[PDB]
Image 1 (tube, rainbow over the protein chains, first blue to last red):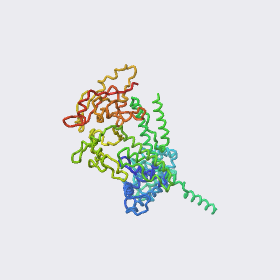
Image 2: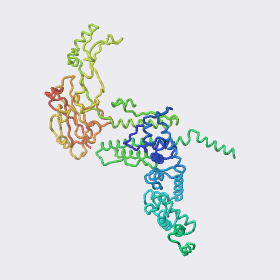
Image 3: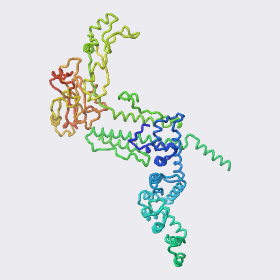
Image 4: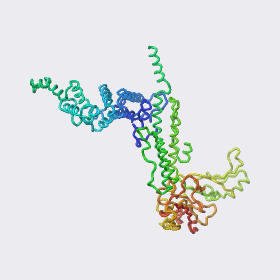
Length: 242
Length: 97
Length: 145
Length: 145
């Protein structure tokens, strides 16, 4: 009450009071939920935090139990804020990457300029991201700070994973040479989470078969219909068997 | 064991229904941290008012005692008043000398 | 304290104590921390609006005010009219708010009351308006020679 | 800056203002410089020895030109009776506030005493007083440290 729009941001002023009533330990997480919810525009009436304060400042009387004309759209906005509070606690993602997932969804594999999703395919990648961060251990801050910038390299991530640096280099090379959807480009090889998750699946398949990633690449080059253009010789099967 | 399950559930139902539950202290912390930050801007304002009185009773404008960073937002602004109370004690010691 | 703030400075639209310091659902906890912030916002607003006043005295002679007065409102001499408004009990001299008559109350009938309009004193034209628009009484003292 | 003319403002045209440069007063040469380099105004009080009709008081504003480091309102002062007066109703050195003009340097500045409603042909209250005024006297109290 008594808020000037010019002096401060609405969502940052409103973030302590949202965290006070959504049972959030952090005001920064509450600011993330308000930024997220402005991208969703939840409810029947497409609710933004600016529309939410215009309703409170004009039409809401505190303590009165009456029917305001657009009260049910406000409730759906507050039901949404509690939903995304639950998304944060259930996925186990940390506070700073949840900023990054709200503000830069493309860095987590979403389309360009797209609002993020609390889809079940998007909840499963936040959990697999949070499991990925927790596996990094004490070097997880150095990876996420280099992931928030575009400075994350294969040599740096392999140090935190206790892998060989040439293993993630060769896994990145075989990911860029093969037809992935979405593609793995040297620009985003360690910038997007989808590309990082793709490169690590070259690592996990190679560790399972106890081969190098180019041994896996030799194996997927023996695909029957992919090699109806250039048929592999018996020697290429004989080398891949060895 | 079915009694212990029901006894565990009664303690869990007690922690959620008591007045001094977690939802109270989320409300208390979220509201007080909003008050404490707004009260911080008011008290630094008068620490700067006392410095302007120090700069006017003595001819000096290059002499500053209230320096930024009493509020550390990463630590919720804790020890902001202890930092300013030291800064007020450095004006008064400089005034007496 | 807000009424004292609204009276030391000419403003009535400026309010600092706002409802909802008491939240009954949280047993009214942090009600004093909310009010102590609100008291600190009056005092910060008071310090930024306080001025050294231009403290002005002005002596007003009611004989001069009643003599110098427009002729359609009936100017008069104070010393002459009182001497005959005390001799009879029914007199009334002057008009408007600059008159001199007896009281209209019950206990006020035998009391001579001399009345002066502030706007007819023209006190605001003594200093130019570039100095200050707020011009307010500090003290009135009476001399009856 | 030692002139004597009418004001150049809008409401200031009928006001006679007498102006004095501090550097032409040569106050710093009164005591030798071994005592103290910081020499600053504590209080200025005005005396206007003039044929004031009793119960008809003088009206004047003592102002300072810069308003630089002064508090809100410390740049000006009002003269009511003109007999060793400050602007204040009661003078308090033990008051917690700065006095008007307190802290101004001895060396620099320009001090101006303005008499509103001065001129005779455009009719003003203060016309007949200023014809009888012989000199303007300033009691400057300052500080050497």
